[PDB]
Each structure stands twice: as structure tokens, then as C-alpha cells.
Length: 41
Length: 492
Length: 50
Image (cartoon, rainbow over all chains, first blue to last red; front, side, top):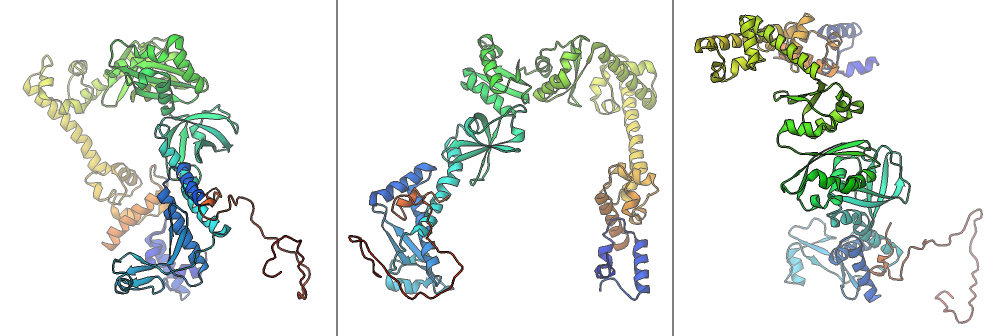
């Protein structure tokens, strides 16, 4: 629900989620990077 | 007091099939625990009850061990042997200790330990002791009626349960009513009801017949099968080895008196009694009673039987809501298709025409030769491909070269279907592509490829949402296959 | 639940199925016990405090 929940998940965990493609994972990284955040903090 | 102690211990043993020794060992452990609770410092206690007087001595037990971890409860073998040279590892050293006064506290501790073997375990013990009742028709008194189950009292602190599915659909029991039922399962719920009793299952019918028909109890007549629609209708199949005894007549009894006693106990359930035959077709004819069967066709490969009846008997053969055919099918173990003589002939003509069309299309034979193959009993391309060459050579007009050519054509017709299964579907070519994703058969690979997912890479690029409309693919199975595809494509 | 018929082996007496309960007193007042009188009808065993 929150950005703080998303930032704790690893890239390998997000790829296990249902309806989660490589394209949507790249979108999430690019958007988090635009805000100075990274996956796995 | 002295004799009263021993008499009480004997009464516990009698209450729920226990032992005087097992009751005393447990009272000793109970008293040791009660003395250890009173003792502020946690120290091992050993109580010994004299079996003649009921007097008891309490010790400070010292578990003789090799290495002492708990100096308050353990003593070394060397130190134990200094007091008594006869002691071994695992024995107890004692110490003169004041026995706990038997107040209502110790009384509550010891009587509960005795109740753990003569109230909760008494339920299980009584069920086991009644080895006949466990399996046959036990009799209980209704103690409590709930929405989902009935609790029965069997006596001796044994409680049984009838579940809602284990009752007949029209039975209404009240507290205090006597109920018979088969003990079909003994579990381990000593506290409560470990015994499960049924009135709905077929075993209730079998055991009622065993009690009502002496010839079944004497093993002169055997019940081979029983099929049951509880509180409505049942069928039983009976056999005898004695040619002097009619097994159906014995189970019916004088003017139906025996079968009517069983029916009355089952709330007016209609019972058909049929002769068991070792021929499946003759046994199914008997099972279809009271409907007259005109012909039977047996399909051994599908384990099915087509039953032709006269148009006037069709409604009787099916029965109310299919009850007669269903009970006959459950009794025989065969799937039973009931139709008219005219419908059976129309079905056989349609099957013969479909076989002729199949053979003409795939074997490149004329309709006359395809008709001869169907008249000789060949219905499938598999039969023609795999049947022994001798059976095909018994057909008038077939020579060894023509049989070999027919078999080669039949195998090639199947190889053309296997080529589609390999590529178009996914049994070889697309098995390492559209079906590479773990959890996808040849059918699923062709369903994926119909959506444009032709490769293992195409599947790795999908979302669960893109595959959600594929018939037979759950979101979990889609997610597993996409992850398997990604593991191979992106992490291999 | 603890069958008090096996009492003869442990407690003794006969059957302690009777509700065991000690007459305890109610609330509302504090105090300090200053004087205790014990009167005994003659024939009854005097206990140690009497």
C-alpha cells in the first residue's frame, strides 16, 4: 500500500508476484530512481 | 480404610478396563507431583503405595546418573553405591520425607489421574472391550441432539457420535431414545466421543442382514456387494456355495418378514435382494430388477454397459431420479447406460457409420471394405494398428500383404495425429517452447500458442492477467509457469 | 471430573464430591483485630487456641 512497503521488497520478490512482468519491474525501478529510492532498502 | 483403598483401586480397573498396577503407578506419580508442588525447592519425589494396606511412603528421589546436571534431583552412581551397593544407573536413592497429608488437594490430583484412565480412557477402553460392537450394530441412548451431530451414551463412560451425514434423512431423535448403528471408526478422542457411528452407510445394511438372516451369520450366504440411497432404497447382492439354499429366499424370509424387519429399522427403506453372478452381464441383469432387460452391450475398454429395455420398461429401469440405474451401477461397479432397443440400434448404426467414415478417411479404403472391418468388430484405428496379425488374417479376403499395408496405414494415421500433437500442440517441438513453462501439457501449449505465446520467452514476458482467460489455467498455475519460464530464460 | 469414588485410595473419608469451600467474609471496612473470644459448649473438644 505504501512506498515504504515497496522499497523493502527485493527485485527477486517482486518478480514472483502475479501479473508482474519484466516491463512493469523496469517501470517501478525508473519511477523509484526518479525519487531517489531503490528496491531492497 | 485399609481394605477400602484396595477396593477403590479394583473399582477403577473394573470401571474402564484398566489394571490395579497401572492405577497405583499413576497414583504414585500423582502424589509425587503433589508433594513436589508443595516443596518450594523443585526436588524429585518418589512415592510408593503398599498394595495390601494402601499406606504410602514418600522419598526425596535421586535419579542415579553418570553425569549430574541437576544436583537437586540427580546423584552420581559412585555416590548412590556408597549408600546401597545394589543400585544401578536409572535407579532412585530415597530420603525419609514426610508424606503429604491426603487433603482434598491431593484427592483432586489423584482422582483426576485415575479419571484419566477410568472416564476419558474408559470411553476408548469400553469401545475396544466390545470388539463385536466395534464394527457391528452397537446400541446407544441419545444423550444430546445438536444441529450437526447426535451424542450417544453406550454405558461405562463411553460416548459415541452420529454425524449429520451418518443419519437417515427423515430420522428425528430425542434425548432418551434408543438408537442402533454401526461403529465404523474408532479414533483417539478419549475426552469426548472417539467412537463414530453410522446409520446411512452400506455397512449398516450388511450388519442388519447378518443379525436378521442366520444363514449370513453362519457364513452359508455371503453378501458380495451393497449399494444404498439412505432412507429411500438399497440393493444387496447375495451368493451361496450351497446349491440346496436359495440365497434370495433366505434373505427375504417367510412372506418377506426378514427384509421387512431390516426395512423397518431403516425407516421404511426399500431393499432389493439380487443374486450375485460371476458373469458381469448376468449380474447387471439381476441388479436392474425389477426392470426386464432386453439386451446388454459391454464396452470393456470404457468399463461401461449399454442396457436396452422395452419402451414400456424404460421409466422403471431408470427409476425415480435415476435411482435404479445409479444403485445398479454402484452395485456392479460398471457405468450403466439405459436406453430403448430402438435407441441402442440407432447408437450402433451411428458408431458403425462414424467408424466407416474414420476408416475410409484415414486408411484410404473403400466403404465396402470399411464396412467389413466394422462387421468383424473393428471400431478404432488403434485396434487395427495393434491387434494380433492372426485376428486380421481370419477376416475373409485379407491376405498377409494387405494386413501389413492396413496396419502401416493405421499406424501412419496415428503418426499424423502425433505430428500435430508434437508441433501444433506441444508434445515434442513446442514441448520445449510453449510447454517448457513447468505446468503446461500439449493442450495448454496449443492454448498458449493460439494467444501468440509460441516460445518459452513469450511466456516469460506475460503477466498473470494476460493468461487469466485460458480454460484450465488458474492464476496460481499461470504464476508458477511464468516464473518457471523466467527462471530458464533469464536466470539459466 | 476427578471421580471422588477413588477417594478411599487417596484422601480417605468416603466421597468428597460435596462442594469444598471455606466460609470467607465480605468487604467495605478495614480494621485491626483487638480481641477474640471463644466460647465452647461443654463436651466439645477444645482446640489449641481455645
